[PDB]
Amino acid sequence: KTIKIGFNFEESGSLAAYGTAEQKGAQLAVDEINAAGGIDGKQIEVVDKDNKSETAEAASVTTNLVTQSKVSAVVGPATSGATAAAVANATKAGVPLISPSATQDGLTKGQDYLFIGTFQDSFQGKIISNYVSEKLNAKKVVLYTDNASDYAKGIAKSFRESYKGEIVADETFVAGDTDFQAALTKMKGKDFDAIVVPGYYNEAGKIVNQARGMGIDKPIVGGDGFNGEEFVQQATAEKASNIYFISGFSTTVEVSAKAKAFLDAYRAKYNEEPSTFAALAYDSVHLVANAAKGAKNSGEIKDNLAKTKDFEGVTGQTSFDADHNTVKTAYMMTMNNGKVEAAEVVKP
Ligand SMILES: CC[C@H](C)[C@H](N)C(=O)O
Ligand SMILES: [Cl-]
Ligand SMILES: [Cl-]
Ligand SMILES: [Mg+2]
Ligand SMILES: [Mg+2]
Ligand SMILES: [Mg+2]
Image (cartoon, rainbow, N blue to C red; front, side):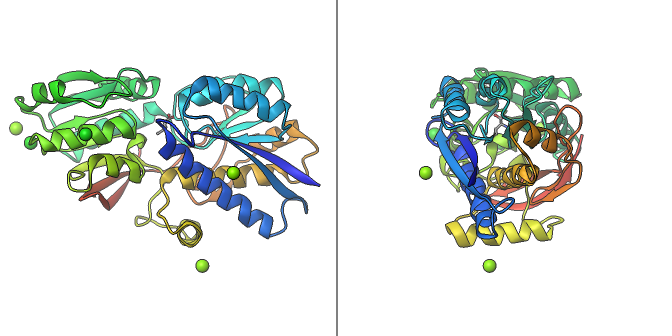
């Protein structure tokens, strides 16, 4: 027999770069585990569903995975809105759901069936404030945020709380926008030392593109939403200079053997570079597979995940606390000409 595992990922739509990276990293882990004999001698059977980057679809897909497909665990969604919309449906069926990358604070509170593989937005905002203040030496900044996003708003809230310099402009945009001219024009005529942009790649990359196009050269700093090659494609490699952003995976600073092995394996399998989201998803599959060893049913997989205190993976350790959260190493990436040239370990 087999062990059924569902994927619920943003494989198409506005968040596709994130979910597709996770699909690739998760599938690589499954393939390897299967080649090595499966779990308890059972092959992993994947039911891979695309949530289209939509919250209602993420919810519907979860119901179908847990009640029709009758999967034992779900990996994904990648993003916070979708994860928040999926959790109650997994919970009703008593199936654990692990999001490799949903950073919304408090998402796991009281959620016996939700696990989060990454850090939180409060942590991101604090790191951004510390970095722009102490490393970019910024006494004045522009804050430009996706107002249609709880993710972006959470990072912005934390940033404002921590930052002691002057926010000279606190402007907005919304997901789906493709024109940022008015706001950028308004910013240009003001002295500032950096622009902090909480948001996702479709908007952030276009913002970088347009800012640099109109002569704004100062540092543009983002949260984890800046990861991936689609951000660089939107910005264009030329304009993707003086860019800094948070990541949970680095190929150069304090690089572990597991990170090296994953980079090599992903390149061999896909002939592409992995993002931090592929790395987190690869670890999430291993966390579930390990938890499935000796598990008689889905509640036991959940219990076993909750007892995971010392897992070592591609993204360092995973050690779940009582709230199903794990501390994770974070890096501030330095990007020029669309390439990461430096990585610095950072913490609040
Ligand atoms: C892919 C994850 C994204 C960038 C974000 N951390 C979220 O929670 O929505
Ligand atoms: Cl553009
Ligand atoms: Cl400038
Ligand atoms: Mg398929
Ligand atoms: Mg000045
Ligand atoms: Mg090899």
